[PDB]
Image 1 (cartoon, helix red, strand yellow):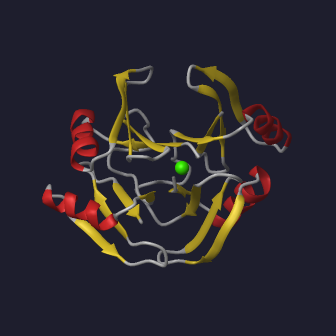
Image 2 (image 1 turned 135 degrees about the horizontal axis):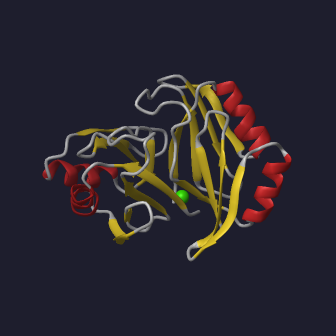
Length: 114
Length: 114
Ligand SMILES: [Ca+2]
């Protein structure tokens, strides 16, 4: 089911480089919006998208925690991320799936769960 | 595709009352956990869930913005919310289904889109 979450970033261009080019989420839109540059990405195969925003000051840049996105191969994702210079915690098993966390340039933590 | 977001609340019992009874989300879990009480809800038929947490310092209670969840009937949701005393911003028209926003007791802003 469709869901959209707003990730607080300090520099939208650097965030685009990270999420689209480094992590490999697909770019869905990069166009003017009501509050600023509307920059929207989503994992391939997913119906959950992230908007990389800078206009919600109650959410300081890099403050996001506690987000998990489904993946079909968390070990593959982690190997690719570490190869590309990204900090990764995990993978680790839980009763609810096999999960890992990584941080974006501002410190937002993105979780992946298989 | 599965996704999980953490919503920062202050009074977890009040938040449970709000998300489960006022808004009408399903209760998926309510049990003691590693970082605190694990309280998890989700819209009916959704694969996106919300965990109502109080343990992320970078996410103060009520600070969350920019979250949008699918609904099949935004007008019905708004009618139920207003019957229960919740102010609703909207609903207002969009290129594919109308949307609406409202605040939880802490001030987190939740969006629904048809
Ligand atoms: Ca989803």
